[PDB]
Image 1 (cartoon, rainbow, N blue to C red):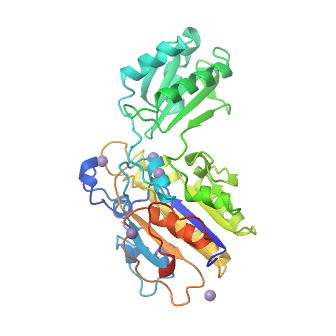
Image 2: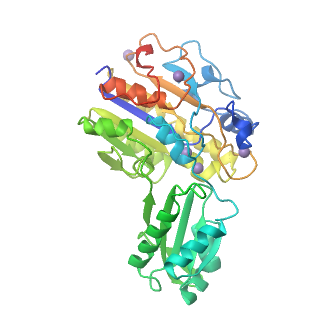
Image 3: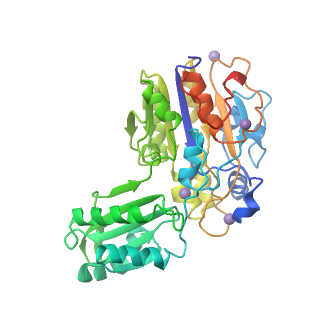
Length: 391
Ligand SMILES: [Mn+2]
Ligand SMILES: [Mn+2]
Ligand SMILES: [Mn+2]
Ligand SMILES: [Mn+2]
Ligand SMILES: [Mn+2]
């Protein structure tokens, strides 16, 4: 192998400006890093700058450097959709024609009618809401009636809440499996069904850790599958295992925050492994992008950047660091959905004694998968062109 270890970091939703096909999505004018930089009167990201972030694109507080530590470019999404699954699945070598849908006005009556028909239960709610909000509003009615609270987030999810003392957990799980079956339909294609059991009394409801998820497997065997099948380590950090439904994962490390994510990345740097360490930093998307909070997003990016020098110090000559994103989620954009954007790509190894250069623009996210596959000598993905030789 050229590199013994590849550390892949997805800064979730950290887009670098509208893609050529942004108009189709209602995403004209969308710039995630750029609008955040303007809100902050200049972003403080000196370590990303040293890597060459400004060399990809100059933004307020983010300037180009004469000698970037590593190679740099941006990537264009080839798949139809801009959702959580699509971006990650493409990164690992796939092409996804069928997008996962979001439901800002709730689910179609046709879907909910069939769920009622199959379960013999009434459905209430049917709106985007946080767990706390929907239980405060509907928890009591749910307890008294034995109905199901169905709700969604700003991402492609269908969540079903029921009180543990009113609907047995095993019955809730059975209902979620039915919902999972009904939502494998492009009429209303849902990424994830989530059981949301709760306990307590009116005015004091709490969700329990008895949450179960019902996810879809990637539409194809991924580069992670190939690595695992060839006895390489595939260490998933954060939501990565969930996103791929465990496919090709050899170890999964749960994280509770972006800072915790970086701690787990550092943990993997300290591990003797051969293969891929794959981190998703989700706070950018989950806390700040969807909530249209440019201040919080900017603070999070600055907190993330400050962690990087320790990562640089720990990288070995035969380690490669790859930093990218999955889509955009511009915190100063209408609505609550993602934005169709280019994503940055930074590729750094301490063995790059002369620093890096500009790479040709990556025409699909699958170029990452192709590079990883070529490095470890496993079956190449159907899509994607490796840039390993350029490094
Ligand atoms: Mn838009
Ligand atoms: Mn994402
Ligand atoms: Mn999202
Ligand atoms: Mn050196
Ligand atoms: Mn390309």
